[PDB]
Amino acid sequence: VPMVVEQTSRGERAYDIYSRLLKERLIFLVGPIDDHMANVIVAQLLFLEADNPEKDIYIYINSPGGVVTAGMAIYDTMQYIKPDVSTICVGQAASMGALLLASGAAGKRYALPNSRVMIHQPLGGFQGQATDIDIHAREILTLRSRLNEILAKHTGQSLETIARDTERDNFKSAVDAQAYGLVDQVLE
Amino acid sequence: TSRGERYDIYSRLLKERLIFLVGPIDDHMANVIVAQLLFLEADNPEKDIYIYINSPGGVVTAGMAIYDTMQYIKPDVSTICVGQAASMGALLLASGAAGKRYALPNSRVMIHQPLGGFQGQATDIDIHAREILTLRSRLNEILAKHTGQSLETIARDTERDNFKSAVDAQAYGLVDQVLE
Amino acid sequence: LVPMVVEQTSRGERAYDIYSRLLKERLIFLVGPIDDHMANVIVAQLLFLEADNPEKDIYIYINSPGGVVTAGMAIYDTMQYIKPDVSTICVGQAASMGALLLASGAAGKRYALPNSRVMIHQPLGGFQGQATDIDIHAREILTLRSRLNEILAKHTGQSLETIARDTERDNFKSAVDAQAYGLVDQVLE
Amino acid sequence: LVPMVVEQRAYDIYSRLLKERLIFLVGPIDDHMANVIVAQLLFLEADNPEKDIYIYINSPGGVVTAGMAIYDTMQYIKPDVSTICVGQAASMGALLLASGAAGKRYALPNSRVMIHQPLGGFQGQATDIDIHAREILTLRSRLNEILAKHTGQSLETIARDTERDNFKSAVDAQAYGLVDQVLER
Amino acid sequence: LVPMVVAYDIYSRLLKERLIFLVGPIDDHMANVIVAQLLFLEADNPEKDIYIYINSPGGVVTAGMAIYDTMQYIKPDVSTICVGQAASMGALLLASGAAGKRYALPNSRVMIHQPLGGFQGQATDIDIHAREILTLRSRLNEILAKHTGQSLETIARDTERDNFKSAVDAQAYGLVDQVLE
Amino acid sequence: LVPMVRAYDIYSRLLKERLIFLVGPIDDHMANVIVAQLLFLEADNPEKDIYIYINSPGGVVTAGMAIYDTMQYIKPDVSTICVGQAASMGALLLASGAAGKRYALPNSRVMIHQPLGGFQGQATDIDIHAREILTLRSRLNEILAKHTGQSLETIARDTERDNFKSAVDAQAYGLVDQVLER
Amino acid sequence: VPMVVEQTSRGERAYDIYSRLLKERLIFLVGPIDDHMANVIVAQLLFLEADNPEKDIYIYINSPGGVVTAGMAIYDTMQYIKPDVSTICVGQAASMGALLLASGAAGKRYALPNSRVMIHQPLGGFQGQATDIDIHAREILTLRSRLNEILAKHTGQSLETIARDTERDNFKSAVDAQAYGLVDQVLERRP
Ligand SMILES: CCCC/C=C/C(=O)N[C@@H](Cc1cc(F)cc(F)c1)C(=O)N[C@H]1COC(=O)[C@@H]2C[C@@H](C)CN2C(=O)[C@@H](C)NC(=O)[C@@H]2CCCCN2C(=O)[C@@H]2CCCN2C1=O
Ligand SMILES: CCCC/C=C/C(=O)N[C@@H](Cc1cc(F)cc(F)c1)C(=O)N[C@H]1COC(=O)[C@@H]2C[C@@H](C)CN2C(=O)[C@@H](C)NC(=O)[C@@H]2CCCCN2C(=O)[C@@H]2CCCN2C1=O
Ligand SMILES: CCCC/C=C/C(=O)N[C@@H](Cc1cc(F)cc(F)c1)C(=O)N[C@H]1COC(=O)[C@@H]2C[C@@H](C)CN2C(=O)[C@@H](C)NC(=O)[C@@H]2CCCCN2C(=O)[C@@H]2CCCN2C1=O
Ligand SMILES: CCCC/C=C/C(=O)N[C@@H](Cc1cc(F)cc(F)c1)C(=O)N[C@H]1COC(=O)[C@@H]2C[C@@H](C)CN2C(=O)[C@@H](C)NC(=O)[C@@H]2CCCCN2C(=O)[C@@H]2CCCN2C1=O
Ligand SMILES: CCCC/C=C/C(=O)N[C@@H](Cc1cc(F)cc(F)c1)C(=O)N[C@H]1COC(=O)[C@@H]2C[C@@H](C)CN2C(=O)[C@@H](C)NC(=O)[C@@H]2CCCCN2C(=O)[C@@H]2CCCN2C1=O
Ligand SMILES: CCCC/C=C/C(=O)N[C@@H](Cc1cc(F)cc(F)c1)C(=O)N[C@H]1COC(=O)[C@@H]2C[C@@H](C)CN2C(=O)[C@@H](C)NC(=O)[C@@H]2CCCCN2C(=O)[C@@H]2CCCN2C1=O
Ligand SMILES: CCCC/C=C/C(=O)N[C@@H](Cc1cc(F)cc(F)c1)C(=O)N[C@H]1COC(=O)[C@@H]2C[C@@H](C)CN2C(=O)[C@@H](C)NC(=O)[C@@H]2CCCCN2C(=O)[C@@H]2CCCN2C1=O
Ligand SMILES: [Cl-]
Ligand SMILES: [Cl-]
Ligand SMILES: [Cl-]
Ligand SMILES: [Cl-]
Ligand SMILES: [Cl-]
Ligand SMILES: [Cl-]
Ligand SMILES: [Cl-]
Ligand SMILES: [Mg+2]
């Protein structure tokens, strides 16, 4: 957890490497998506918006996905705040991670040459995470359709195409993800 | 802990009167939220406070501690549902200052109160049936008051362990506006 | 994760956790099960605040299911001894030792919030030995139970016989009913 | 909660009270906490060898030799060491309470004191140490002699009464000679 | 205990000199920290070389690929030094440093072999299927062939056996440019 | 919980006054910390005495020997004070303080006996063999005989028994020079 | 781990005891050798070289040994950097710890009077530490020979002597380690 120190007008101040990159409006979405990591990302997005509502924000995504409602919290925050939120896939983006990648500002969604994208949403992401919550079948079907509609909107694919392809738990290459409309450009 | 030395990201947002109510509700996190509310009131008793809620609910008496603090302090307490709000989280969402309760478009709200929230959390305490029924009625009355629904409607609907969409929560009176 | 509030001092920044910041305004939090560890921190806070200003009121906000009797008694004795008035506010709940400490605040300065609940009942668990090599014997339990009843009768104005009969019941009183019983002076609404 | 205060430098609440020559002896007595108390006693003596030191005791007792380390340090250092029982003091905790400077041993009204020394306190705490019967009898006698000296009770009285694992009230502890005064306002 | 120097911990102090340590098994957590360090150093100075010292048995393929893609994209040359060992993804990243700036110490060892473990799903709900494994194995061989100068089939043959190369043999194979003595 | 007094912890405050605490079981981790403290204090002032307060049941022999060798090498006199107890390696280090500057408190107890546990391998891949144990036992006995003034034969006989000496009896035996009273 | 505080121009600055000694070019190699602790030692060696490539560095060794390749990372760094790296055995040095002890700058390898040195290399140090790595027999034999060649070079013993003696899992005393060529001098007394 490396640090970097900057000498300011009021002394020297230390950051961890992630906080230092946050100073440059860089957010890291890494690891499984759950409530804890989704809320810290929402907090970072809101912080950057208040600091400057005009400059783009960048989310670097390396994630196998995870909890749907946690991912939706990030999605809604990305869409609401004034700044454009650019997304870059490094490593992989699956399930909710793939959805958030595809939901970056139009024209500003990127994948690196060896990254991979899987839109498939496993059952695990829809189930209750709290002991006392049982997520029922109809709520799952509603959420699955809602996610498909979001993907269709941001990719330009038809709803029927998204619904067919999301059943398959296969990865798309960066080139294939770009052609599908999940990202705008492969960075080479 | 996205952190600088000499705030973490949450403490930094607290400086702007923003409180995060995230994860299961229990005594530990409820008392931290009570402490934040009291701090912000003393710092400025006129300015609005904002609680962003992403919670599956939890312990009833812990949630009631937050509810009573929200109602007593002078500042308006605005509530925003991000992700979900269930049980006590849903109640606290609906209990924000009138006109200042918000939900994001893909958030979901479930008023249903599972048994787990009423049971004793301490080893030596058994919460008895009559106390559970009293608390359930009190929660229904709080929801009816803040939503504008009748006591029947809350009492009938709270049996269903189902989520309302943001639009449906707004129509029900659980929030005032969907931020879109 | 406990939030910080950091202030700028003469040569940089100075950080408090949220509880330490509220302590600066003479606010003490009694939260969770009562045991030796948390009781001694509360005793330490009370003594600190007295030395800082022996005249100004101290406030203890109570959200506790109770716990160890002797740990609670350490707080009780410290509250009574120090010069400042100790005001008590029930938030959430106060049971067993938590209810006793709530009822033992300075006269006229004991408060409950509208949805808080108070149970004076003292379960056996609070009287048993907490150390491996300590067995708390029956007569010591009966002595402590009577002592607690006498403390409650004194601070509530109820008779000893009323307290002894009612402390049986493992029932909660509402904030209004606790006020009528003499456990608090006023419901803050 | 490890609460903080800032003074004109930051302290935890216990460190802040240490600045006022206040030491907390809380929880089971073992080597780790006894050595911290010894260190605090030595620190306060060097800072000012004249002013009284105060040890507030809330403890069920514990390891005998660890308590003896505290006892020997209390007796050696120049300052009077005043002792205050809050909550309870048992076994080594009761011995240390009774061993404060004469006239400066206090108990709060609802505190309780038990001199009884259970076997557990005498047994080896290290894996490779077995504390043998004669060493236990020697330690028990020394503890009884220490209590007799500081209480004014006879050795025979201490030896008989320490067998009983009963608590004394604060008033009864004062009458027995374990403390000098019950603090009431 | 990680030592400090004046205040930095030793690793943060070396980061100030554009030194990154890739140590231990490669997974998402450590790969993202390395990506963050690479991006920080590029922004601080996009012209000065960056150095990654590698002592790793390898690990998760996609995590390593995240490091690879970041090394290739940023402007600074990324020099690589093998200390101790480099296996699997560790060996690939070592071989992927800037041409002419890949080093091994005399008693270092390099194994390009990629065990199955690195390709399997690390998340509970992800099953990495056979054809995706074959695609990744092929990509890795192509990356090694490009940076070593060996032919694709030569890499495919040699990566099958889980043997280490000495520093001298790794240099002759094209995995590093020079043995530092 | 360690109290503070920047904030020092209480032990760091006392290190500023050349006070080192040897407390708890002796192992590599705590022995190296004590060695580091001894070397720091020597470099800070090679003339002033150093004080080690000992409350320990003993422990790993080679770790204790690291402390012994450092105590003997450095220029400052190293004074030792037994508080609570000193057993096995703890007792050896107590007896190995600077001549005339080894102290015990009135209720402290000292046991020179060395249990088998201290000689066995602590690392997974190390087996300490019988002859190495006997060599170390002899080396420890010679150290005790040298610093106490007792004969080697006396040490070898008395170390066999797992019994404690009182502070007075430890002083008479030559394990400490003086019992501190008043 | 204790702290020492030094007064600066702006107030106080704190070190842990090990970091304070690092400021005087002192490195502690303590406990089992593995990748994590070896990389910290490599980092310290490189820092001290850049801070001053002329002054000696000191490694105090109290270790039962451990992972061979992690120790080799330390060995290669000691040999490459410009400063002489002096080694001092405190307590014990076994396997890789003994090799690194013997690999200090010629004339600057020391043992304390009650320290002990065992060159024997147990199988455990050669086995794979990661789940997916199996270290095969010939690689073990190659590494064992390489270690024997390093010891023969630095001790002056013949390769055949090292190979024979290393089989035995016995400790040498400080005096015997000095006579064998594993250290140059036993620090018996301070001059
Ligand atoms: C970092 C320090 C500032 C914190 C940033 C908060 C913020 O951006 N909230 C979003 C609401 C939101 C929350 C969330 F968790 C996810 C999400 F997608 C959206 C917001 O509404 N932003 C406002 C500016 O913020 C505010 O006006 C206040 C004050 C600020 C301390 C936090 N206010 C709010 O949370 C809400 C309640 N905002 C408002 O009161 C206004 C008034 C009508 C309701 C919504 N509002 C807005 O959209 C305002 C009007 C003009 C632009 N306009 C924002 O961007
Ligand atoms: C950081 C420093 C300020 C911290 C804020 C504390 C605070 O707001 N407490 C609530 C009581 C409360 C606590 C809780 F946990 C939940 C909850 F819903 C309500 C409160 O009463 N606030 C007072 C202002 O605070 C005070 O007057 C004092 C001092 C302060 C250190 C805390 N006092 C109190 O605890 C209570 C007992 N205050 C009072 O005595 C006054 C007069 C008697 C009735 C209660 N009081 C008030 O309500 C006063 C009247 C005018 C404004 N008025 C508050 O809001
Ligand atoms: C941060 C610096 C001050 C910390 C506060 C300590 C304090 O108030 N202790 C209580 C005793 C007590 C302890 C406890 F754990 C629980 C409890 F309910 C009561 C106390 O006695 N307070 C004194 C003022 O403090 C003192 O005089 C001394 C010095 C101070 C460093 C701590 N002294 C004590 O511990 C005791 C022994 N106090 C006394 O010596 C005096 C003299 C006769 C015995 C009791 N004393 C008092 O009551 C004094 C006399 C005037 C008022 N009077 C206090 O409030
Ligand atoms: C914050 C820095 C100071 C820390 C306090 C140490 C201290 O008070 N040690 C006790 C011995 C002791 C240790 C212990 F763990 C428990 C216990 F009950 C007693 C002590 O002897 N105090 C001395 C003053 O301290 C010293 O002279 C030296 C220097 C100081 C760094 C620590 N010295 C000692 O450890 C011992 C060895 N003291 C002495 O050398 C003197 C000389 C004759 C032997 C004993 N000494 C004393 O008792 C002196 C004589 C009168 C004043 N006199 C102390 O109180
Ligand atoms: C102040 C701290 C800077 C931190 C460095 C970030 C960085 O270098 N990102 C890479 C993208 C990347 C991310 C990753 F995780 C791995 C990887 F291999 C590559 C990048 O694109 N760098 C840019 C310079 O950075 C930017 O322009 C912006 C702003 C900065 C805050 C981070 N921008 C970006 O994330 C992306 C989206 N960059 C761009 O917008 C430009 C526009 C065209 C598409 C990509 N861009 C570039 O390639 C720019 C223009 C030419 C050189 N060119 C970079 O090096
Ligand atoms: C805070 C900075 C100084 C840290 C103290 C180190 C120290 O005292 N080491 C002992 C050796 C030792 C280590 C150990 F872990 C246990 C032990 F019992 C003994 C030492 O040798 N002390 C020297 C002074 O230190 C040095 O000269 C150098 C430099 C210093 C950074 C560390 N050097 C050493 O480690 C060794 C190698 N010392 C020497 O080079 C000299 C030269 C002849 C061989 C040993 N040396 C000495 O004895 C020197 C010469 C005069 C007295 N003389 C020390 O006190
Ligand atoms: C506090 C900041 C400096 C940190 C010290 C790093 C260092 O000394 N690395 C060794 C290589 C090495 C690494 C390792 F993990 C173990 C090991 F045994 C050896 C090194 O090469 N040192 C150089 C000076 O450092 C450098 O020139 C650059 C820059 C520095 C940030 C780290 N460079 C390097 O990694 C390598 C690649 N060095 C070089 O580029 C030069 C060029 C020719 C090949 C290797 N080099 C050297 O050996 C240089 C030339 C003269 C001596 N010469 C060093 O001391
Ligand atoms: Cl129910
Ligand atoms: Cl009984
Ligand atoms: Cl026996
Ligand atoms: Cl034996
Ligand atoms: Cl060992
Ligand atoms: Cl073998
Ligand atoms: Cl094999
Ligand atoms: Mg000496």
Image (spheres, coloured by chain):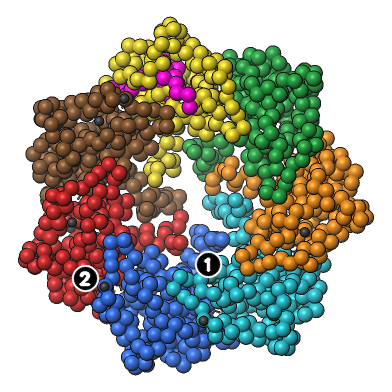
Chain colours: A green, B orange, C cyan, D blue, E yellow, F red, G brown
In the image, what residue occupies the spot 22% across and 57% down? F116
Q: Residue under circle 1?
A: C37
Mark 1 neighbour class, 10 Å CA radius: few under 14, some 14 to 19, many 20 or more: few
Q: How many numbered discs, if any? A: 2
Q: Position of residue E19 (x, y in %)?
A: 42, 29
Quadrant in the picture for residue G158: top left
Is the Cβ of the residue at disc 1 closer than 8 Å to that at disc 2? no
Q: Position of residue F174 (x, y in %)?
A: 14, 70
In three-dimensional space, the C-alpha distance between marks 1 and 2, rounded to whole angstroms, equals 37 Å
Placement of F109 over or under A80, stated as above or below: below
Magenta stretch contains residue E102: yes
In the image, what residue occupies the spot 70% across and 27% down? A99
Subunit bearing disc 2:
F
Q: Which residues are magenta?
A: E89-117
Placement of G189 over or under G150, stated as above or below: below
Q: Which is closer to the viewer, label 1 or label 2?
A: 2
Q: Which mark is residue F163?
A: 2
- Viewer-proximal residue among D132 and B5: D132
- Viewer-proximal residue among D107 and B114: B114
User: Within 8 Å: ligand 3 and the Cβ of disc 1?
Assistant: no
In this picture, residue D169 sits left or right of residue B139: left
Task: Please indicate, yes or no, whether residue E41 appears anywhere in the rendered image.
Answer: no
Amino acid at the residue labelled 2 = Asn
Quadrant in the picture for residue G122: top left
In this picture, residue A10 sits left or right of residue F92: right
Placement of E36 over or under A112, stated as above or below: below
Task: Please indicate, yes or no, whether residue G145 appears anywhere in the rendered image.
Answer: yes
Quadrant in the picture for residue B107: top right
In the image, what residue occupies the spot 87% across and 50% down? B157
- Viewer-proximal residue among G46 and G159: G159
Q: Position of residue A88 (x, y in %)?
A: 63, 24
Q: Position of residue G51 (x, y in %)?
A: 33, 34
